[PDB]
Length: 68
Length: 68
Ligand SMILES: *[C@@H]1O[C@H](CO)[C@H](O)[C@H](O[C@@H]2O[C@H](CO)[C@@H](O[C@@H]3O[C@H](CS(=O)(=O)O)[C@H](O)[C@H](O[C@H]4O[C@H](CO[C@H]5O[C@H](CO)[C@@H](O)[C@H](O)[C@@H]5O)[C@@H](O)[C@H](O[C@H]5O[C@H](CO)[C@@H](O)[C@H](O)[C@@H]5O)[C@@H]4O)[C@H]3O[C@@H]3O[C@H]([C@H](O)CO)[C@H](O)[C@H](O)[C@H]3O)[C@H](O)[C@H]2O)[C@H]1O
Ligand SMILES: *[C@@H]1O[C@H](CO)[C@H](O)[C@H](O[C@@H]2O[C@H](CO)[C@@H](O[C@@H]3O[C@H](CS(=O)(=O)O)[C@H](O)[C@H](O[C@H]4O[C@H](CO[C@H]5O[C@H](CO)[C@@H](O)[C@H](O)[C@@H]5O)[C@@H](O)[C@H](O[C@H]5O[C@H](CO)[C@@H](O)[C@H](O)[C@@H]5O)[C@@H]4O)[C@H]3O[C@@H]3O[C@H]([C@H](O)CO)[C@H](O)[C@H](O)[C@H]3O)[C@H](O)[C@H]2O)[C@H]1O
Image 1: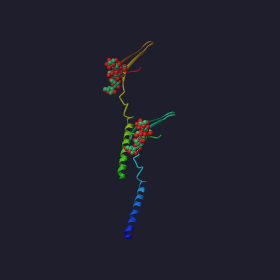
Image 2: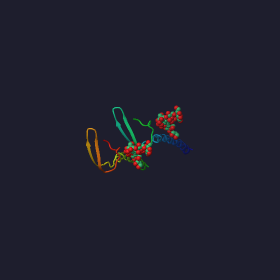
Image 3: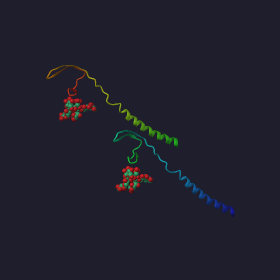
Image 4: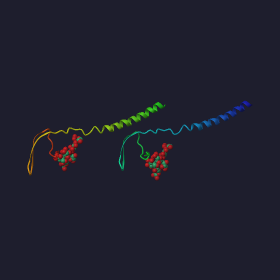
């Protein structure tokens, strides 16, 4: 009797460890993305205005997505 | 994995630098031309008239292109 019952208990424990491991991995598998951007920018500053002129960029992006 | 991805990023950066350089060169490659002219001119001045008589010139040019 007892060696089979001990085996059933060890299977039950194994599933909870595997379920625990899955929640540990979830802290690694997020928030990685390609955020690199590169632009040719020139600028001139005066007592009233900043002028900004763009010559090229790595990608086309919305002017609302850029913070100054 | 990562050495190939790093290489792809460096190619993307390289193109933006080359595009930047092309706009720098554009400030040199304009406004150079052969503007030299030379004429045999004689003149006489009076209380009412200036007389101007031309004997030869380096090229034939319109009288509207000359400022006095
Ligand atoms: C999962 O997989 C999916 C499918 O592939 C997506 O890829 C998803 O990624 C998300 O997608 C959503 C939806 O595309 C993104 O939400 C958008 O976020 C942008 C911000 S962003 O910087 O431009 O990138 C915008 O906020 C966008 O909103 C649009 O709609 C706004 C409201 O317009 C709605 O209502 C008007 C009436 O008032 C209707 O006429 C119109 O048709 C539409 O229904 C606009 O205001 C907005 O304009 C400006 O928005 C931002 C400022 O907020 C600005 O930066 C922009 O440049 C632009 O000038 C823009 O036109 C979001 O889209 C969703 O739109 C729904 C709407 O119901 C239509 O479905 C909501 O109302 C919200 O507006 C918004 O959720 C999200 O960013 C992505 O992560 C993957 O995760
Ligand atoms: C790119 O490559 C091309 C091809 O090689 C050229 O080399 C180009 O260089 C430019 O070329 C253009 C065109 O030739 C040049 O523009 C001329 O500029 C001169 C000034 S200049 O000092 O003489 O060198 C003139 O302004 C000339 O205009 C002529 O036409 C005028 C208008 O006449 C038109 O309309 C009447 C009706 O009213 C028609 O009857 C007529 O047929 C014609 O269609 C005339 O007024 C003008 O007379 C006087 O002009 C100047 C004073 O402005 C004076 O200095 C002259 O001595 C002369 O007495 C002259 O006859 C310009 O030619 C263009 O003509 C077109 C017209 O549509 C015909 O195509 C426009 O209407 C303009 O008149 C003008 O653009 C330019 O200078 C060069 O840089 C390279 O860059």
